[PDB]
Amino acid sequence: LVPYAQGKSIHQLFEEQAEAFPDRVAIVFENRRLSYQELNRKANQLARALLEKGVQTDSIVGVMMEKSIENVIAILAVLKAGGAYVPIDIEYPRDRIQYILQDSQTKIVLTQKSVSQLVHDVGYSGEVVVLDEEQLDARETANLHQPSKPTDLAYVIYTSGGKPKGTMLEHKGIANLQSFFQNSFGVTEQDRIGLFASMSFDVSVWEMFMALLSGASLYILSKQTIHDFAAFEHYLSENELTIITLPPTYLTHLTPERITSLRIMITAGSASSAPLVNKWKDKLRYINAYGPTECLVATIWEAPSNQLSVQSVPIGKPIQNTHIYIVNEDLQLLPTGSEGELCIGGVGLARGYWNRPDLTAEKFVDNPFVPGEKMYRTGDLAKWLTDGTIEFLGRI
Ligand SMILES: Nc1ncnc2c1ncn2[C@@H]1O[C@H](COS(=O)(=O)NC(=O)C[C@H](N)c2ccccc2)[C@@H](O)[C@H]1O
Image (cartoon, rainbow, N blue to C red; front, side, top):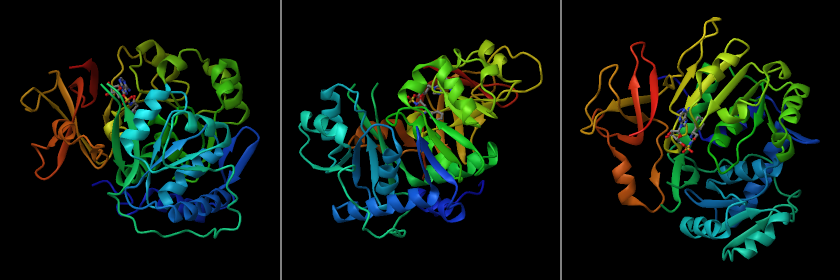
């Protein structure tokens, strides 16, 4: 076992950073910023308000907000109250929003003034908390210390293949992720980390807690900054951001020379390409990161900074405390060179799919190699290379 904070919750790890780095910048959005102490206090105030409204272990709390500092306060508050959040994309079709609200059965939705009309337009019948109406400045600001377990729910991400399905992720996988980031990327409180992905895409979880579980600062990129490639490059350079994660298609539009500060560039979610990697791997640390939503992230490949061109782009090796099994249709293990289904075991596996027991049992099978554990069948095709890295080959 690679060490990590085995018994600690996500918010407990955040609180350790706020205690160690109270006056460091935690989060930036446009011309606003909050220190760790300020962010923690505001999240504690909201968390107490959420407790009074029934949030408890494995409660799912909907979030319908624009990306902003208050969006992150809402997330941390839900975790501190002992619950789990479900990010609901306010740009989805109304009927998809309604499906997620109704399927999740959430009894509380956190929103903002400019979004409250949409909440009414989807006919949501639960409790609605308009955060920029609430005056919480009077509430206690200290940490709550609610009961928590690593196996408690932390977030539910809806994805679609059929109808949307809620993928249930627990605290323990994100606690492991903290140690992965500190060990493998060397993340420290000095880093400045962009937030690029939608909060409905679990890459945003990776980005947000990359910053907030290590004392680093999280720079929430505005819509206009992302839309304009030169504005994006200027924003990263002016603010001296050190780490960013991007879709490969977005990265193809960027110029290394116009980004002066990055030490790590991660691409995730889609296949990268040898020409793309060769353009960046000798200017900074280029990382290809792979995973299904059902364990957030499973493998990483750091491209070699050796002034020699690569001809292909592996998805690399399992992250700490994650196991990869490449198997045939009978779940038998394959030798190097043989293509099979990529399956995953380890601490980051989702609990399953919300109120979908048969689908959960089909996809999160008994681990044939580790009695008493589960193994997730990704549906991705892959093979081991002779050097022990993994080549991604699409879908089985
Ligand atoms: N690096 C890849 N190369 C090539 N195909 C890929 C790759 N990363 C995913 N994929 C594909 O995308 C699927 C998962 O799609 S997803 O549920 O929308 N999640 C993501 O795309 C992001 C993923 N959860 C994640 C989050 C944070 C860090 C790393 C990865 C995988 O099963 C693969 O088919």
